[PDB]
Image: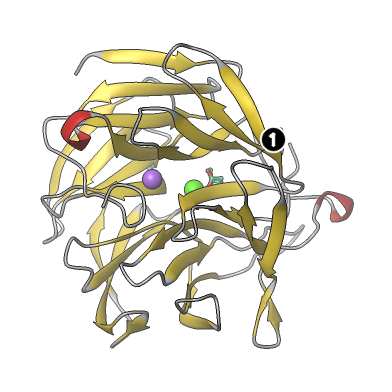
Amino acid sequence: SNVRVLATDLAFPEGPVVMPDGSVVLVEIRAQQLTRVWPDGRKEVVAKVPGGPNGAALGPDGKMYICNNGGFGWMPGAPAPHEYIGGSIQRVDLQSGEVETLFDKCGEHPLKGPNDLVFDKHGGLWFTDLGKRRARDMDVGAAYYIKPGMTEITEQVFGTLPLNGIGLSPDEATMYAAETPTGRLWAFDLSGPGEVKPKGKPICGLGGYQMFDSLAVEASGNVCVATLVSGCISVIAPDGTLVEQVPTGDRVTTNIAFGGPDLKTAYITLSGKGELIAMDWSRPGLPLNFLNK
Ligand SMILES: C[C@@H](O)CCC(=O)O
Ligand SMILES: [Ca+2]
Ligand code: NA
């Protein structure tokens, strides 16, 4: 595990997407932008994304899809009314910087705090809703699926505590969602693309005072979840076994993504230190659709 710092002075980094050349496109939630970090050290702003760009994934159209949580109040906190512009799913052209909003509601219900997302092999898009915190109450968590072609958005999970990381098993027959305040990883069986069958179960619950953020799946099927408070990556087997916890040095470790040769480099956002780091990983990551395969 040779650790290296790839970038500093990032304004709450999140949603790393590791390109084939080893460059990383990621979101800076606090600076409200999409940023490109190159291996020669240089950084460039790809696009300004007003609000709270929270997670990213490359899509079948070659554009970067974004979970926009609508904005926080800044370490993040509950957004004062004016700092919140509504949650949405957006799309950014990595060549012009043009930002287009795709969805801001599901049925008659506005999206609250979209957080992270993952494409299935047909181009359907899964994403989590962390909800928003208000003065005396908070939204419940949810997970949504947007049908291939961006034709329809559907509610698949609703009424958990806030949901954060999301991924698919290698065979894409199981969707995983990380429940933030409980440090529980939930597994949902899929009867087919975009459709949960009964709605799921927690396969791992960490002890103590540990919370979950975003995640990435390994080719083995293990789920690697950024773990807040204790500051590590929690590696969870498909059967829920806690395989290991890899310390990162930051209590606010938020996301992980695999890249490099054989997808055996882990790229991790340390959102407390404002850093993007890379780390040797003993096993290869799961190739993401429309990025790695
Ligand atoms: C720390 C989280 O609960 C909020 C932002 C994030 O998804 O990284
Ligand atoms: Ca997240
Ligand atoms: Na990730």
Q: Position of residue 4 (x, y in %)?
A: 34, 13
Q: Position of residue 167 (x, y in %)?
A: 33, 59
Q: How many numbered marks appear?
A: 1
| In the image, residue 122 above or below residue 293 | below
Between residues 4 and 130, which one lies in front from this camera angle?
A: 4
Q: Secondary structure at mark 1?
A: loop
Between residues 87 and 293, which one lies in front from this camera angle?
A: 293
The answer to whether residue 274 is left or right of residue 49 is left
User: Residue at position x 69%, y 82% from top?
Assistant: 109
Between residues 189 and 200, which one lies in front from this camera angle?
A: 189
Report the colour scheme.
secondary structure
Ligand 1 - quadrant of the structure image: top right
- Specify the farthest residue to the right: 82
User: Residue at position x 66%, y 29% from top?
Assistant: 45
Is residue 135 at all visible to an observer of this figure? yes
Badge 1 is on which residue?
Answer: 30
Between residues 110 and 207, which one lies in front from this camera angle?
A: 110
Q: Tell me which corner region of the image, top left, top right, bottom left or bottom right, holds residue 262.
A: top left
Q: Position of residue 128 (x, y in %)?
A: 49, 64
In what quadrant of the picture does the N terminus appear? top left
Q: Position of residue 239 (x, y in %)?
A: 11, 61
| In the image, residue 103 above or below residue 165 | below
Dot 1 beta carbon under 8 Å from ligand 1: no
What amino acid type should be assigned to the residue bearing mark 1?
Arg
The answer to whether residue 272 is left or right of residue 243 is right
Mark 1: give few (<14), some (14-19) or many (20+) Cα within 10 Å: many
User: Residue at position x 68%, y 58% from top?
Assistant: 133
Is residue 208 at all visible to an observer of this figure? no
